[PDB]
Amino acid sequence: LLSGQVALVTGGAAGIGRATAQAFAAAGVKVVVADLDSAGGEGTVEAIRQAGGEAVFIRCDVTRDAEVKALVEGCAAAYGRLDYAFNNAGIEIEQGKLADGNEAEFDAIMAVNVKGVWLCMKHQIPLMLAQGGGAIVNTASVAGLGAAPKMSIYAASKHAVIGLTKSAAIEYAKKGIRVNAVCPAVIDTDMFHPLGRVGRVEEIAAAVLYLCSDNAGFTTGIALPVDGGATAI
Amino acid sequence: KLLSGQVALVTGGAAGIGRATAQAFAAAGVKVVVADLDSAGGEGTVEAIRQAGGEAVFIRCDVTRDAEVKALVEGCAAAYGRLDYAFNNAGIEIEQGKLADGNEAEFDAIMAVNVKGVWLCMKHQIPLMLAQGGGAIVNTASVAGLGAAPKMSIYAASKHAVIGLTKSAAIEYAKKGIRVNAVCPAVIDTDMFRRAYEADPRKAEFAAAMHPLGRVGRVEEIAAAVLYLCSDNAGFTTGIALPVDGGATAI
Amino acid sequence: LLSGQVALVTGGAAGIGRATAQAFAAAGVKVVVADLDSAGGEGTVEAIRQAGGEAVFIRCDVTRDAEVKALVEGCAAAYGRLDYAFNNAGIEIEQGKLADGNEAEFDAIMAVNVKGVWLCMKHQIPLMLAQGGGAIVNTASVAGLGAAPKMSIYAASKHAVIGLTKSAAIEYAKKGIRVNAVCPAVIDTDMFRRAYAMHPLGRVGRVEEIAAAVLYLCSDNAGFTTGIALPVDGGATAI
Amino acid sequence: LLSGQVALVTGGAAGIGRATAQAFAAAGVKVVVADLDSAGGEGTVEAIRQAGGEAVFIRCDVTRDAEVKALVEGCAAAYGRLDYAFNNAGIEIEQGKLADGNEAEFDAIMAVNVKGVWLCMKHQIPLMLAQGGGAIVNTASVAGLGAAPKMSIYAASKHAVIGLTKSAAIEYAKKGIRVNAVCPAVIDTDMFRAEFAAAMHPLGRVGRVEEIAAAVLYLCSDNAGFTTGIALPVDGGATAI
Ligand SMILES: NC(=O)c1ccc[n+]([C@@H]2O[C@H](COP(=O)([O-])OP(=O)(O)OC[C@H]3O[C@@H](n4cnc5c(N)ncnc54)[C@H](O)[C@@H]3O)[C@@H](O)[C@H]2O)c1
Ligand SMILES: NC(=O)c1ccc[n+]([C@@H]2O[C@H](COP(=O)([O-])OP(=O)(O)OC[C@H]3O[C@@H](n4cnc5c(N)ncnc54)[C@H](O)[C@@H]3O)[C@@H](O)[C@H]2O)c1
Ligand SMILES: NC(=O)c1ccc[n+]([C@@H]2O[C@H](COP(=O)([O-])OP(=O)(O)OC[C@H]3O[C@@H](n4cnc5c(N)ncnc54)[C@H](O)[C@@H]3O)[C@@H](O)[C@H]2O)c1
Ligand SMILES: NC(=O)c1ccc[n+]([C@@H]2O[C@H](COP(=O)([O-])OP(=O)(O)OC[C@H]3O[C@@H](n4cnc5c(N)ncnc54)[C@H](O)[C@@H]3O)[C@@H](O)[C@H]2O)c1
């Protein structure tokens, strides 16, 4: 069970973000859905509303500080508080081994996957501090825990997400903010293992909700693999 | 709904983390077999479950004894017909010195309960779960399974070993419907720990200072992690060592 | 022992980079020293030459693709090939917890510590491919293995170095290119004395201890060692 | 590059242990070769002596406290001190997945691989303390860092080696004793002498005994004084995934 009232999900227009927004709402939480994709983001808000939940869509490019600042202000204006943040927007666009990549790809992946998470947390934390605490979950990857051949920039970016996650967890541990990362392997989304199958968006959402749950109060600074056994070998 | 399995086995269920997790399973609607050397504490866990409206039974078992563990798993099927979830949580922590100051009796005792006990339990749980087409196992490791434990080197070795058993079994049985995970608690406030720091408050001050959160963990927090690892929507989660540690391993 | 002929050290004007440049040269390797700090970089080369070794300084801002390209080609122009690369240039400039940092600090740290390593590797690898091999060592940090309070951007950047390292190690494992990261804790350099008992050993590390770890990772008998993050930390990560 | 005078190598009669004993001796260190196998052990000593080095053989079952104590005493008896210890004796004997294993296998693997390392360190440490320091390397495995299907007891045992290593490293850090683990993947030992195991390494081959020996010597080297409590994978990329 979740007793906080408001969650923010970035990248909530599709895939893991949409599923996790829906899961928060089904648990009784008011959800701000943030994304570049306004069509999909309103699609997520409408699915929540048709199921009996509360949700608003706010368009935001997480690479832009002013828009992320406005997004967290929008959370406060819409619902008065922010208890949970799922910083999940990310991209994966590489086509080759490290020597065959280009600087445009590097810049784009790092901007969304690292700067986006950093900016989001940078603006979420003061609002959570004002309320006496909160819980943040960042989407890393099994590529944040080991090699990702032909996705070396992506792996660098998801490693970096774990570094931000652990550092913020320690910095704000005594201030009521928990910070964790979920580390999916291959998940059946549009961006698309010892168990012999790929994972499902509902399985990532369930892990995010565990990390945000009332009885996860002692869980902070971890990178939770949801990976069908991939990192165990 | 979150756990659709019918039957859980908790070893070390007479006290502490095991007692609380047995209660958490029962509160979720699961019938619980409580296994322990401590008959009094074990029947006490069962009584608390029953008074709360759940179902449980106690089966005495020394997890270091192969014949007793085999009979314990047989007793689960006799009592409730199957075994969906197993929490292999019995363990001891008895060292008093640095590595060169420990003794072979301590080594043998710690390794027997903490490693052989987990191995025996899995050895007899897995065939039952194979026959059912699936099951989930959670083993109690520790933050000492993930890093040094000064003045507890044998304990650390034993909890590292639990993670090795966990990951190996997770890969071996992944395609047979069995998931195997480990929970890695830091210091948890059990009834025994509380008695200890009531007599010596420095133990509470020191233990809280070991964790970035500035407190020790709660038995209900370990229980909730175990139930997550057993939950229906944790079907893609296997072979992990989940720290529940107030940030301790993030440092 | 090291059978390769040519090493490149970025951030070689000072500290860990200077000591590792000197160590390569002591092992008989010709060294290209690269840094923004020309006076320090020429100082490293002067010290190597004064001890009987061979080295040259090439000024390079590792955040700039064209400068890194010219630097790597300059290695081949000076000495004919490039067998070893120590991608060690880095900065540490944060002054607050995550929510107190600023975007300029983020951009600067990520540019040197992540883009610099990525650019260096992407232009070192083609030469090593043509050679049938090489050894790359990237300077990560214990901050790439765990939290670094009040240095969250730095920790993100050094985590990213490990991701680059492991990914390239797998990509090129069958092409003879080993890629590893050394992970120092606090080392007694100007980066440390600028910032002004956390280490179980009771002291901070020495630059020659990092250099020795780099040289092990580059050594002929390290041919089965790739994709690792080697902590040189007085025990810090073992807790 | 190694200023210590005396190294002890357990499991020194064959394979990684023989190779590391030879490497120590080639670096000018005096070597105590320790093993159950007296014939292979003296063979290691003979190879060292043929190359101009200094070694002796001492028989020891590392599962027996009295023999391990006598082994360390024997190091001091032969050479006066003990600077380096490579606790490398180990076995790998399982035949099936976890539920198909047996208790005799469990007991044997844990006794050599865990108790043997524990006993060795327990008796090495006081001698090193009295000298003002020393360096210990324990042989773990990639199976100490992840799953080993059909070798679950072995994986448990090598995980345990890493736990002993890290704990002792922190306990004795300020007393000058460094404690590290080397973590080999598949190594071409005379027992190994197939193509399937080679292919599961990203490098595409199995490792050489000389590559493990060189990692042990780095961990014992004079300029490894800030390296302690680590598990060093020598694995052709296996653990980088
Ligand atoms: N197999 C997988 O899908 C997989 C595996 C590992 C990690 N991940 C990570 O999971 C997270 C979600 O992945 P997904 O599979 O649901 O991807 P997805 O393709 O379904 O969409 C992710 C969302 O992020 C949005 N987005 C992208 N850039 C944005 C930006 N600058 N600002 C705001 N929104 C932006 C997109 O519009 C999209 O709605 C990502 O961070 C991804 O890297 C995914
Ligand atoms: N701070 C903590 O409490 C902490 C921290 C890390 C790990 N752990 C681990 O949590 C698990 C339970 O911890 P706890 O604090 O609740 O301990 P506890 O002493 O309060 O309960 C442990 C139970 O295990 C039983 N037991 C011991 N040996 C047994 C045997 N051979 N056969 C059957 N039962 C046996 C005991 O009778 C006891 O009821 C253990 O594995 C422990 O190592 C605990
Ligand atoms: N000293 C420590 O405690 C410590 C700890 C962990 C990691 N590190 C890392 O070790 C490496 C070396 O640091 P150091 O301790 O020797 O400090 P240092 O500042 O003395 O050396 C860093 C070198 O990198 C150069 N440099 C910076 N930006 C550059 C750029 N864009 N292009 C080219 N050169 C550039 C600098 O001029 C300098 O000479 C860095 O990557 C650092 O992040 C240091
Ligand atoms: N593929 C590999 O070879 C591999 C991989 C990972 C780890 N390891 C580990 O490397 C170490 C050496 O392995 P190896 O491949 O050289 O094996 P090996 O069988 O060739 O040599 C092992 C030596 O240990 C000795 N030994 C066994 N039990 C002993 C005991 N109780 N007391 C004293 N000596 C004993 C043996 O007599 C033998 O000489 C072991 O710890 C092993 O577990 C080996």
Image (tube, coloured by chain):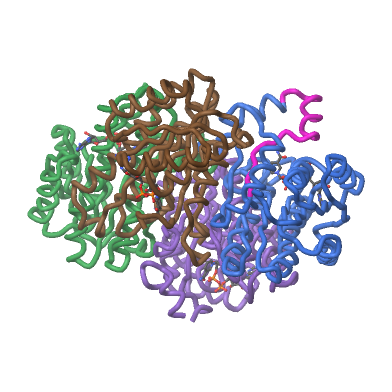
Chain colours: A brown, B blue, C green, D purple
B187 is within the stretch colored magenta: yes
Q: Is residue D203 left or right of residue D70?
A: left
Q: Quadrant of the C terminus of chain C?
A: top right
Residue C134 point in image, percent of width and height? 25, 60
- D191 is higher (above) or lower (below) than D70: below
Q: Nearer the viewer, residue D201 or B228?
A: B228
Q: Is residue B132 left or right of residue A194?
A: right
Residue at screen point 38% across, 43% down: A43
One can see residue C1 in this view: no
Instruction: Place residue D109 in its image quadrant.
Output: bottom right
Residue B97 percent location from the top left of the image: 71, 41
Whole-percent x, y for residue A107 in the image: 23, 43
The x and y percentages for residue D35 are: 62, 69
Residue B114 vs A72, above or below: the answer is below
| A175 sits to left or right of D93 | left
User: Foreground: A220 or D229?
Assistant: A220
Q: Residue at x 63, y 60 (%)?
A: B165
Relative to the observer, which residue lies in front, A129 or C144? Answer: A129
Which residue is drawn at the image coordinates 19% and 46% (left, top)?
Answer: A104
The quarter of the picture where the N terminus of chain C appears is bottom left
Q: Which residues are magenta?
A: B183-202
Q: Is residue D188 above or below residue B109?
A: below
Q: Residue at x 42, y 38 (%)?
A: A45
Magenta stretch encompasses residue D5: no
Which residue appears farthest toward the left when viewing the image? Answer: C77
**Residue at the right extreme, as displayed:** B40
- Whether residue A215 sits left or right of residue B40 in the image: it is left
Q: Quick check: can you spot residue D203?
A: yes
